[PDB]
Image: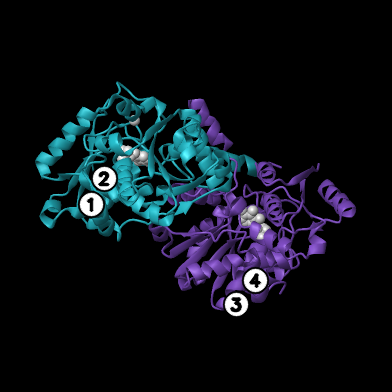
Chain colours: A purple, B cyan
Amino acid sequence: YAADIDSIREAQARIAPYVHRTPVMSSTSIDAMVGKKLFFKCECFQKAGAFKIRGASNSIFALDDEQVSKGVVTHSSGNHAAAVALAAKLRGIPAHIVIPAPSKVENVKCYGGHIIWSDESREYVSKRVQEETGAVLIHPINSKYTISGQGTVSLELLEQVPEIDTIIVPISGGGLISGVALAAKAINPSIRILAAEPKGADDSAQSKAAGKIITLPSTNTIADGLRAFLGDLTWPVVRDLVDDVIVVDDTAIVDAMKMCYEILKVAVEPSGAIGLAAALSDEFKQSSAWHESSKIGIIVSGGNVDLGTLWQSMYKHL
Amino acid sequence: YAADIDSIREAQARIAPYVHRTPVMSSTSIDAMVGKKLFFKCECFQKAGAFKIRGASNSIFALDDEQVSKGVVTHSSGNHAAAVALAAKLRGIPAHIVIPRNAPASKVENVKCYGGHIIWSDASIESREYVSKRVQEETGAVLIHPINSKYTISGQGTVSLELLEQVPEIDTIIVPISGGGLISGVALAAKAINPSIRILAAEPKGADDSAQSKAAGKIITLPSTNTIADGLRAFLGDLTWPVVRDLVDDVIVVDDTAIVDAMKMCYEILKVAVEPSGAIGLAAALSDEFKQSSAWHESSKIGIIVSGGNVDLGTLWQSMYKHLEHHHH
Ligand SMILES: *Cc1c(COP(=O)(O)O)cnc(C)c1O
Ligand SMILES: *Cc1c(COP(=O)(O)O)cnc(C)c1O
Ligand SMILES: [Mg+2]
Ligand SMILES: [Mg+2]
């Protein structure tokens, strides 16, 4: 596979000065609903509001002196942008960030990212910047270094809760779940890894059922971080090391988000709540994975969400 | 004073099996805005969504078997109602919770959630008290104070025992104030551990009786209150006032738009789903009043007590359910 336990441990050593060891939270009330013990790995509390700084940090700090000196570049409309900007700030090198985009821009400026605006056009702008500067491209999902950084989530989780027997992971490009599964399977081959995916962007579930990478002409989900398709380095992990993809609709995602805010008191983004929706779902509850499970890790992947509606009403109230 | 370091340590041992040791969080972004290092003590992650289970657990578990046999009773439209119901549930005893009939549906649900025996009342304090008195007469249940008692103050002081162990370098603590139970416990424990620690209250402009009381040199009340900080509308009690008078350096008064700004920052930067009352410590830390004060110049490492996360976000959810439909359309 594109990463392994060795590369993941190298990642952990490399990024440990720069990322938070994020907390695990639980709730007896949610536990009762599911009928199992849930452990929420809170990457919403990671630097920049999501897990992606791990992969971005590993990618950037892994570059030698010669390479990194040209800066880094990426095009992104989401959490990857801020992650690259922060990782580059920590390394001391420029980050050229081609946007787009929603708030997610403010997070890049916060880290001194050099924003180069896009309108196709994303790739052309990213392409021109690369040709002229030589800046190294940092991938949101599909590389050894970001997969490896992402797997550190599993190293921490299994230190924090060593009896975890199943892990539910949100899926988009599959970087997070690939790193998580690779690290976890290496520490304990009997751990079950399950993906959580929205109905209107259910390519990963289709892919697994079809035995081949499926792409979709469009996607239809409020889980804005979950609209990508699998890459050629992540699909093999999804195919071989992930038992199943639990598919849930957006209403279930919102229902789960509501629970995160109201019960856990964690201000997650919709994409970060989907693991809980999966754990609450009939599809999961009526399955063998459920019957065999006892202690389930849930990766709460981020918390970057625009709640401007809320604030407007409050300021209107006066 | 009504409590002391020994009471608070007895509280710690008594409640340790029943409450969460809550985490401390920080943010380099917020630190740069204040110009200081902030440490958020997250009582929003405490059982029942707030710190009050500490005081309520202490009060309930301190009782002997016969005392508790007739149950416990309180009156509250807020977080205290649920804290008493939970504490009572943890010991396996009845809780008579006197609630006004017009109390938020969310706060009633939090009581039902813990199996509280609800006794309904009219909205005035006099009504709540009249009902609370009759329940005590009919049952002999023992009254659990939200603010003004040794056991409640001692339980609240465990917040400081944790926080000062978790971040020993803390030199100032900003604490939301309403009846003054939290800040009294926090101050008594913190000062005993380190008498040079600065304790600051954070209070809404539309409910600034603690600030008025400090200036007057005795307990002052207001003819009404006017704040979105719904847990901060009470007045000081005769056991909390002495501690506020002697051990709290200053009351930082902020308006409701500052509170909303600080709540927004809690959500967007810290990723913590606080209630408005729980954000006021950050509003205080961000204020001109604080930044131009002597306390700011003297301070370096500042603890902020994030006191709770129980807030009705119905408006958010309604908009989200609407948005996902349109999105599929
Ligand atoms: C990108 C993202 C994911 C999915 O990550 P992949 O590695 O693309 O599967 C999940 N949650 C959040 C918050 C994200 O930003
Ligand atoms: C009650 C309450 C306070 C105030 O506590 P006192 O002991 O009355 O000063 C602060 N924050 C929250 C969230 C509360 O419920
Ligand atoms: Mg998908
Ligand atoms: Mg007041």
Q: Is residue A242 visible?
A: no
Could you tell me if the residues under marks 2 and 4 are in contact, i.e. CB atoms within 8 Å? Answer: no
Chain where mark 1 sits: B
x and y percent of residue A297 in the render?
51, 65
x and y percent of residue A303 in the render?
57, 49
Q: Are marks 1 and 3 on the same chain?
A: no
The residue at which mark 3 appears reads as A186
Could you tell me if the residues under marks 1 and 4 are in contact, i.e. CB atoms within 8 Å? Answer: no
Q: Indicate the amino acid at tag 3.
A: Ala
* Left or right placement of residue B201 versus residue B35 in this view: left
The residue at which mark 2 appears reads as B153
On residue A8, the disc is: 4
Where's ligand 3: which quadrant? bottom right
x and y percent of residue B197 in the render?
38, 45
* Left or right placement of residue A175 versus residue B283 in this view: right
Mark 4 element type: helix
Q: CA distance from mark 4 to mark 3?
A: 10 Å
Front residue of this view, candidates A191 and A89: A89
